[PDB]
Image (cartoon, rainbow over all chains, first blue to last red; front, side):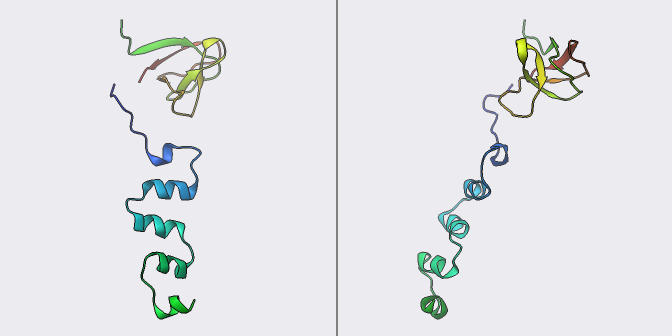
Length: 56
Length: 56
């Protein structure tokens, strides 16, 4: 009868929507895409800014 | 004597396939929250009747 019963993210009944997205994410870039909504701030944190991002 | 299925007095009305957990007085009652699940019923039973279901 198995040994571990590896649950999945959606089995965690009091996890939040952003919380489940973060738990599923594999890389730091993916996490930043979830967490940072302001596109100019995200661009700064990614070290990749256009002239429009810089002005903003 | 490792039993694959038990006969437990229903603490309520139980439908076929319902996941069961402990209830008042140690009776078997329907649940929905994995952790409390110890077995799944294989037959319908009314409160006070035995219900037979596989462990797992």
